[PDB]
Length: 139
Length: 120
Ligand SMILES: [Br-]
Ligand SMILES: [Br-]
Ligand SMILES: [Br-]
Image 1 (cartoon, rainbow over the protein chains, first blue to last red):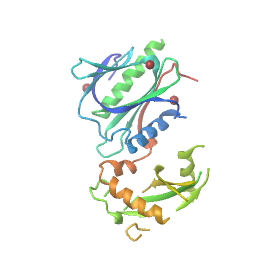
Image 2 (cartoon, helix red, strand yellow; image 1 turned 45 degrees about the horizontal axis):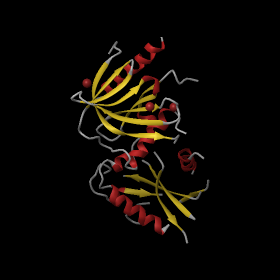
Image 3 (spheres, rainbow over the protein chains, first blue to last red; image 1 turned 45 degrees about the vertical axis):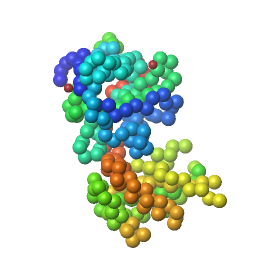
Image 4 (cartoon, rainbow over the protein chains, first blue to last red; image 1 turned 120 degrees about the horizontal axis):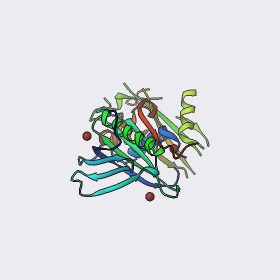
């Protein structure tokens, strides 16, 4: 809700497809479709493991840690995030997934990161804070 | 290059058991960049496109599946029995068949956030 630039969220982690060359992956619909085909092929699971992670969103970008806060898995730097998309898994339980498309410093390779939120409300809050971050650093 | 398509719809779906009578079938053929846009344009003219298997001929022909919303229980020869087998297994995987028949990305997208640093 209106209006913050720094927030933490309890989420689940579906998985990642790291270091893609290109596949010609344009826009949010190609992204969702790609993740669908990965799930169908068994590269990503339909159901995430039970363990919860802490996602911190701020003007640095997105940080993912263990629920104990002890270990940092990843720092997704704001500069290297291309797109985040929130969408319904489409399965029955009506779960909301977040997909992040990130790139590397030289903009030569792409990676996809998929998370599961506990509600649609939470997924939208994460997107709001991320958007606000972008607009904030854009000044 | 060579392609084949098997179109299937249910009458279930979340069901534990695979009942071939719960599903119906319409195989088409087309030659060859865009594969996902390709087959889907061809179907409507006459949900997704799923590559299942390739079949050697002794040079290989591909079999795609197109989920949608002639009964399979009542029922090219190499491909039908392969589809019956493939469905028998995957129906005992959970979420698999529901995922096969789920709505399009556009029916499911909720939020789209882009980084202004990558504009134009
Ligand atoms: Br929370
Ligand atoms: Br893009
Ligand atoms: Br990097």
